[PDB]
Image (cartoon, coloured by chain):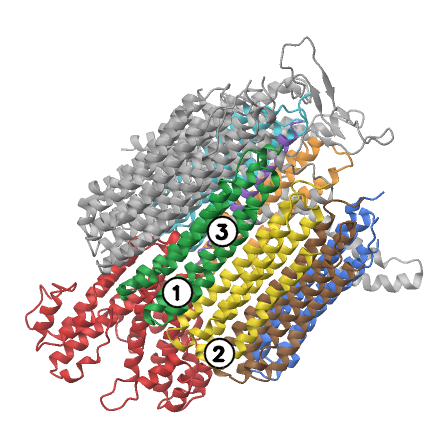
Chain colours: A purple, D green, E yellow, G brown, I blue, J cyan, K orange, L red
Amino acid sequence: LEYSVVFNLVLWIMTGLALAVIITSYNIWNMDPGYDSIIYR
Amino acid sequence: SFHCEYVSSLSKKGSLLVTNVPSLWQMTLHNFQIQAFNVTGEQFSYASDCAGFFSPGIWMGLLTTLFMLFIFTYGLHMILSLKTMDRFDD
Amino acid sequence: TGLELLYLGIFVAFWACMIVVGICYTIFDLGFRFDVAWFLTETSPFMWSNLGIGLAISLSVVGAAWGIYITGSSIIGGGVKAPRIKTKNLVSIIFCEAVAIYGIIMAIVISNMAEPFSATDPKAIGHRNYHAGYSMFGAGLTVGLSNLFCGVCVGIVGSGAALADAQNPSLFVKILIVEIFGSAIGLFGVIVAILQTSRVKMG
Amino acid sequence: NNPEYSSFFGVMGASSAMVFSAMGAAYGTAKSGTGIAAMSVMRPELIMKSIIPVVMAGIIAIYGLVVAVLIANSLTDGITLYRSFLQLGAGLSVGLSGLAAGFAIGIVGDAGVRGTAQQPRLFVGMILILIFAEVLGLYGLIVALILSTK
Amino acid sequence: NNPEYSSFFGVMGASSAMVFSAMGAAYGTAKSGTGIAAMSVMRPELIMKSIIPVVMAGIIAIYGLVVAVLIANSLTDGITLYRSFLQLGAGLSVGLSGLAAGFAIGIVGDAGVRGTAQQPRLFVGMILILIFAEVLGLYGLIVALILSTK
Amino acid sequence: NNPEYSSFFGVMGASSAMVFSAMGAAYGTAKSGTGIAAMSVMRPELIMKSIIPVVMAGIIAIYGLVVAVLIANSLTDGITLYRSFLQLGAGLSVGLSGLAAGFAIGIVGDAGVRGTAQQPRLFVGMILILIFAEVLGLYGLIVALILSTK
Amino acid sequence: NNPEYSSFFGVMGASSAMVFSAMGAAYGTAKSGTGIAAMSVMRPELIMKSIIPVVMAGIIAIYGLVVAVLIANSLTDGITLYRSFLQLGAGLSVGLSGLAAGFAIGIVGDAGVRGTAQQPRLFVGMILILIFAEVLGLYGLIVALILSTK
Amino acid sequence: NNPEYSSFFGVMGASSAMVFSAMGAAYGTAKSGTGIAAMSVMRPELIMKSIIPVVMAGIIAIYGLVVAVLIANSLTDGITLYRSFLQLGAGLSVGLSGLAAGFAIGIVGDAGVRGTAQQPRLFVGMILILIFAEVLGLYGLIVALILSTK
Amino acid sequence: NNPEYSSFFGVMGASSAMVFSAMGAAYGTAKSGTGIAAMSVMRPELIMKSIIPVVMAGIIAIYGLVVAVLIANSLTDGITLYRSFLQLGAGLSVGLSGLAAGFAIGIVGDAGVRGTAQQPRLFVGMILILIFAEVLGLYGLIVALILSTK
Amino acid sequence: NNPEYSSFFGVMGASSAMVFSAMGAAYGTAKSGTGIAAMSVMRPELIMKSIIPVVMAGIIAIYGLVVAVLIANSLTDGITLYRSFLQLGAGLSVGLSGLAAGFAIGIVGDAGVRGTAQQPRLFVGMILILIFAEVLGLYGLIVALILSTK
Amino acid sequence: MKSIIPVVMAGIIAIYGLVVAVLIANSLTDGITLYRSFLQLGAGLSVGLSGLAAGFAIGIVGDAGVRGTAQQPRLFVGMILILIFAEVLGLYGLIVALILSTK
Amino acid sequence: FPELYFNVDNGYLEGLVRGLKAGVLSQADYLNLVQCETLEDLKLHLQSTDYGNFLANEASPLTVSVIDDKLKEKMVVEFRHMRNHAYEPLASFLDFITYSYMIDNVILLITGTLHQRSIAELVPKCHPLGSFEQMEAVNIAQTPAELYNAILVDTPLAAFFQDCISEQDLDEMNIEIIRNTLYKAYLESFYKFCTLLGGTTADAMCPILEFEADRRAFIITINSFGTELSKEDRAKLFPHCGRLYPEGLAQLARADDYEQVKNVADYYPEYKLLFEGAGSNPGDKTLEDRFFEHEVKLNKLAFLNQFHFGVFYAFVKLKEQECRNIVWIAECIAQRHRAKIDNYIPIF
Amino acid sequence: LGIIHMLFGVSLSLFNHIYFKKPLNIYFGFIPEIIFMSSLFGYLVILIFYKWTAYDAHSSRNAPSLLIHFINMFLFSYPESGNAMLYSGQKGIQCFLIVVAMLCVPWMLLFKPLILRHQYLRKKFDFGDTMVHQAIHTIEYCLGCISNTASYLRLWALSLAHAQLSEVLWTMVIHIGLHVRSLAGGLGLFFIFAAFATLTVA
């Protein structure tokens, strides 16, 4: 018993953590590196 | 067949046994397993468990949460789409 | 980009998992799970009823707000060079607000149908009572989304009318017929929700 | 008798019938109305011809209404599960075809009024192209009547 | 004998035959109708020739309708479960092949109509290409007829 | 007596009433503050008049507050699911309505502020359009006052 | 003896064989029609000779049909699940290979046709790269025949 | 009687108050700090006044901390689900109201600060709209104090 | 005895070997034919020697055919899960390694052909690069032969 | 005695405290380092003052380490769910408040430094703004310490 | 020859991953106690994803820092100072991972 | 579907710019301006419409140069006021409009430094839309090589220079080849950028840019036949985003006579009609004037869609055509040569 | 190794401040800095050597974990339970060394700024600027103690990686060169080791 509760804890906590990692990782990986002083020379 | 962790009259163990009236009796079948038609040999067939991936309380919960997260996402998509001017007038 | 990839990623991962689950429950012979009957029966009728009531408002109000922001922004943007716009074109705002009022009427009617069952078992609840819960959800969702689309429609065509009026005033009354065909959609959402509600009783 | 959840699919029939036809008719009208209003500045006389895409998108809302009325007048707590699925088929089949017709009407109405304002000879072509768009709502209605009244 | 829910698959058949054929025909009509509308400003005489894409998009709608009517008249209260799945198959087979045919009639129609206004010789080429777009609907229909009557 | 989870739906009700109306009023205030900034550089005297869409966005979040307080004062452990779902209904109904009205106040506010700056005849027009936008928040409030007291 | 759901996979075989091949042929014909249309503006003579990318997309549509009829003619009540999985694998194997071939015929058909206008010597190259695109539909057939008749 | 797992909701309450209030105050600060540092190059005298959006962003995080502490010091092993959900409701209700206020403080901070350098009169206007952005965090607090004390 | 579903994974293995390698060889052909066709206007003679990327794309589909045949001939109703899983692994291994080889052959073939058009020396280089692409399909085959024969 | 599997959330608390604060500090460091690097070309003397946003970003990773270590030291196989959740919520509270603070530190570091090179008076302002960005991590830590030790 | 530093600072993140991967892998067994197995998960994520955070931190400040250094040689010291507070994120993932792996 | 977001940020300016387009001279207004005898009558007519008071606080010995500059002043204040308001999805698009003037300012800057003239002397000649954000290039002016390096840092134009202009090319190339090769890169990039703004913006902006690409191809070709530009140079300047790109451009590169250009134009009805529409006969409208008439047709058509940024581009080009019309009328009035005055292009 | 070289580093600081005649730096910096470091490090190093002598295979069952006692010492939070203590009176030693280290920070942070304030008031720069700089330096040294200690784990990390790369290269390349006949194995090993040597160099 409680197995639907264990599962809906672990599934949704892990999907929340995995989205927080994925979104943050996507945001930093596609962050502007900002080297405008040389990108044109 | 059927399997359950606690066919019991106690709330601490799921309250599967229900009395509509006061009772002098209590019971618990820890890991209860039963099969009573189309049995073969002395071996149980595959068991449906009393606990699946979801429950009535969880479906009501998710059909709210994973509905209002659609609505909060609309909130979040418009608020995150706020912008500001890069210039101001002469 | 990022939010589109997030919504696409969730949508794809969700439906890919429902394909894998649908195949796996089928081929393992677990058709005694995936019991949609259990889902619709043990999920409380009060939930369906109240999602119906709250959506009948909020989706109608989401439509009417979308409608107001669209036509009201062109009204103001054109009204800079044509101050006459602010009066006649206000009908496109009043028709957006009518779409919310269609929502409020229909949600109050559905709310007046909601009652306590005092029951916690499917046979004790009984068919009329599940049928109330679902038909109240459906009525509320029908009006709610029909008004959402009607509000999006009225504001859009009201922006059309106000930007045309800013260029030639004689156009407004001639164009304004399109907002009537828009506002018909919300009214049809109300007529259907009335009929879906007309037979229910909770208790 | 029938199961308690029986009427759920039939309710989603009536709701789909109207909502997707409201979505169709709203997009068909919204798109067409932008065309009409923008076009009318150049050619103010053309409004009474150019309303026809909007009347067509209004007919799609009527198709969604017709099937939703017939389904709602055919709902009861006592409904057999077989009829309740047919009512869902009917509601999707008009609703999403009404949506498909609304999309076409909206796109061709806007292009059609814009073309017409430069070249009035397009008007016969526009009416033909709108007939071939709006008839998808009618096919959605035919299939939905056959399901909902069976 | 059979699940009371069995008809649900055949009902999603009838709906999907209609709906996805309507979405095919709607896209075929929207895309080529936009082409006809813009085109008719330069070559007004071509309206009553350039309509052929739209006529064939209507034919994909007709294929959806044929199978959706065939399924809907072939459904019954106690339908045999595999006979219900055959009807789902038929409905997706014509419905989505109709959608695919609609996609080709749409893009071929738009490009072929604009191209024909640039090039009077293209008309025969466009028609041959549209037949190779519209026949996908017909193959969708052949499979769906065979399945729905197996 | 009542189910263990029962009070949760009323709780999310109270939360949504405040959160969603907060998001709406936040957007309302952010758009209006941007419009005020781009307006003030040219028309600094106008600020005390151009505050109207901001204070109206702040009023939208009071409609959320009022319901979130009413729901929260109505909670208890022993709550029946009927009262709990009525309170979730009050929650989304004010919540998303306030959210939507906040979006209309923000966008109409930013325009109305930038428009009034160039054309003083619009100040009353902006006030009127925003009154329609505020009334959409009031409708959410009316049903949420009904549901939370039912 | 055999499972209830067994024929659903056999059906998904037939349907997929058709639907994904129609999608492949539709994409092949949509890109190729775009290319032929835009090419023909300065090349009357090529309108007939250039239709070969379309004809090969029409063959992908037949590879779908062949497997879909071969599966459909072998569906029945008693199907032992194993034969239904074989049929699903056949239907996906031809279907999605038809989709891949259709993608490739589209891209090489567009680019190849445009290039053939610029340089008529390209035409033999366009045939060779198209044999290598069309044969993916044939491999899709070969596997599907083997599976559906194992 | 009290179940296991009760802590999750109350704990996610405490954490959500802190996390979303910190996200709010981090967006409020990031936009304001961008505004201040892009602005101040032309106006050194405004640095020690244009900090106010950042101070108000800090206060949203304090409302978060208040509720997160008030929840964290009111958890117990085997807490009843009613108090635990109330602590979730309080948690989200300040946390997300702080997030919303964080967006508003950010935007009025950026636009109001940058605008001030070209127009000093805007600063008092920016303070007032920034109180209207800040006070949503306070409505979130008021609801969160209420829920956590039922 | 062994589970009735066991053949499914082997069949999805066979399908996968064909499907994912057809997707690979299609993409490799599509990009290669684009590059060849775009080259031809400037270098009409190189279009024959530049077939080689397409031939290697074809070879990736032949590897996926081989494993799809070897899997498809190795199936029976009673197939042990151990063996069916080997076949699924084999299918994905050649299939996705063929897709990987296809992405390589395409990008290398396009850039290599359009480079060789401008630079007659590059041919000797790009064939070595294409070999280091196509060998991925051979590694996939090797692991698929190894898996399917345990 | 009490539930097995209880460890999972406590362990996830340690990981969340570290991972998200390391993401915060990485973003903070990264964004700030682009600022320092691009600035240094114009002002080769400001390098050693300009490190402070990088240092404060590093301190966010220290806060996540402090909680992660405190959690890990407080784990046991027999951990009551009350302590296990308190550890998860502590983990997310610092982890994500540190992420928020890291976002703020990255943005105000970069904007502060690029502004400071154009006007050295901003340096004090960048420090004051940055204290309000960094204290969010300290608040997250406070709640995490209170939770994990409750 | 100087600007290789960011590559080697990224290089240590793989090695921090390897240290924990090896430590976990040697500590596995048939029927491992769940508690010891979750500890190994938490370690494995904590290094792996802090390594990932440090990987991005090094990538961005290495790309900007090397470019900046070629325009201004004085940045060489600022760059390697920045690469401390970048690469230390990999180390903190290691610290917690070792603590968890031996708890 | 785009309508349903567009007015969130652009709704106000969309209303504003259509309102500003209502403030243009109709065909009847041009037919009134030509009725007169002196520039004082141009003032008195324009006083009845949106340009009123544009010659208040100005000297009584009025000149056509003052009317030209004051009409440009109104056009540029009407545009600066929108650019200062627009948000990033539109603000990048309005900046692409300004590039059609910054290219010419860069040619003035390059021409000044090649002639060693101080760049600050040319700032008053540069078009006001093409204002550089950083004047430090202008303040330094030290060498052409310094100007090149300074442009590549100070200006967001740098990404176009990197594709077509090296420092050695900047000295070796003729400035008119630099002007056109820049415009090739701009127009192809602005087209690609518009195809990212999908739906209505692409669908009703792209025809104008597709035409400008073909207009450039024809006009560059016919003007090159008496000149140093080889077959390769014409091809190198033609913009590849026009309808003619697959074939027509290649035939125009091969061309050496106006009959061969007409043969290319005779494949496309849209262009066949321009070459039939002007034979360059005595008293005829020129081929260039037919392209200006067609450009006005396309810009008018862009106002017939609602929710798109195409109206901001079509507005700037129509106000430019209006300035050009008022100045041409004012020249025919001031120079007394009213016989040709009808050569203005009607707009609405 | 890292602890000892950091203890040398603070000792090198003492010499350098003496050669610049800076009594303030040795008094307010070096003394509390070495005490902070030495109290934390000394406990840890003592425990490491003690474990290697105080335990064996017999005492290995239920043997105490060193890192836990080290963390608990810094937390001031051993709960009288869980792991057994390592030696008699160790609780007092934990309490003493951590409290002594915690008492170092105020001297380093504030006491030098206060003396510098009174020197500049009597000799008749700012107090706040001095406080900010000295606080930052103090905090960087103290947080650096933890971080820099852990940074010496790079030693181990690299040493493992080198060993495992070497082990894999041997097992993948050299092992294949071994054969059951003298001539075949002798020819195989020659080319196998040349390929191996190339990979070891790279």
- Asked if residue J148 is positioned above or below residue L19 in the image, the reply reads above
Q: Amino acid at mark 2?
A: Pro
Which residue lies at the image location 31% right of the left edge and 77% below the top edge? L114
Give the amino acid type for the residue marked by disc 1 in the picture.
Answer: Ala
Q: Nearer the viewer, mark 2 or mark 1?
A: 1
10 Å neighbourhood of mark 2: few (<14), some, or many (≥20)?
some
Residue C110 at least partly seen:
yes
Residue to which mark 3 is pinned: C4
Same-chain check, marks 2 and 3: no
Alpha carbon of mark 3 to alpha carbon of mark 1: how far? 29 Å
Along the line of sight, the residue nearer the viewer: G92 or D63: D63
Position of residue J119 relative to residue M35, above or below, is below
Question: Which chain's residue wears label 2?
Answer: L
Find disc 2 in the rendering and name its residue.
Answer: L246
Residue L238: x percent and y percent?
41, 79
SS label for mark 2: loop
Q: Which image quadrant for residue L52?
A: bottom left
Q: Mark 1 — residue?
A: D111
Q: Residue I8 in the image: state x and y as whole percent.
A: 75, 50
Comparing G26 with L175, the one in front is: G26
Where disc 3 sits, the SS reads helix
Q: Is residue E30 above or below residue L267?
A: above
Residue at the extreme top:
B24
